[PDB]
Length: 284
Ligand SMILES: C[S@@+](CC[C@H](N)C(=O)[O-])C[C@H]1O[C@@H](n2cnc3c(N)ncnc32)[C@H](O)[C@@H]1O
Image 1: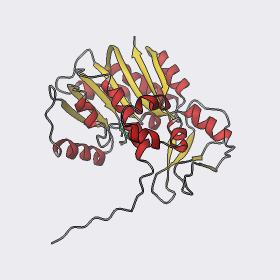
Image 2: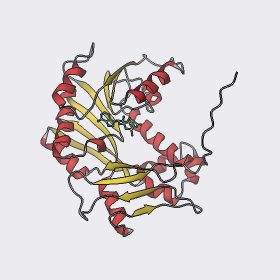
Image 3: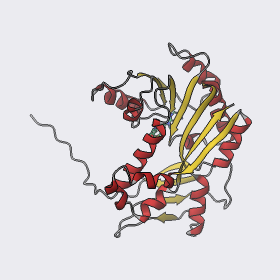
Image 4: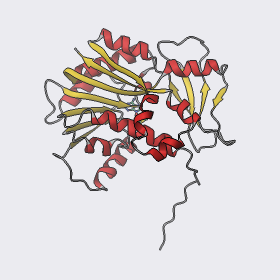
């Protein structure tokens, strides 16, 4: 009897760049070590689960809408055994995070043991763009974060930066349905398809297509995150900006965490990384 699985042959040109992203998420998640209640908005397949465990978070609440992803998080938890401090409890909530923030806050608060006052941190990595659809969706996101947090709680966001993408497209003179491409030794490494007519950054609703790597030109559409607009809506809802910084700024520390991968990062890697950034906000 035999079972065989053949993946497409895939080169390693994304080695160093994806190790940089992992290092960044780890340094961010390390900052909330041993907190009692941490909520993750858009937790997916649990890619950050190893990080949350290494940080000793005590109660992780992970919310996502994709039952398939969440099952992979369950398999990941139960395969792969752990025993390091003191053990994190995990609560997975299957929920569409575009629904009214009041309902989502009620379901979360009904999780056995969730604090009436609220959690200590909200983490969301590469998710908030799904909610940049229109003004109501951004307000909903800020009201949901306000309801789930205790005062002084913090929001730890990670996102593609819409200002930088628009600036990137303009400097390369990319018009409506055209594509910016990275290219390395004659292969398209990264790419962005412009899908907005406007030449000025809109609050909400501007789409681009990002190339999915190792596909044969499959582009997946996302909205642009206007971080100015995001931070401004969060300000209207009781949050102060704490920190806002490009992923490119972790590259020097990265040299101390694997000198090897540091030296292999290419100029296309650095340009792609520059499009992503961290944003910390605190509830007043
Ligand atoms: C880029 S992924 C991965 C997020 C994860 N924290 C990570 O860094 O890998 C974004 C996740 O957002 C989830 N998502 C997209 N739209 C959503 C919605 N309306 N409600 C809840 N989750 C959503 C997807 O299921 C996906 O797992």
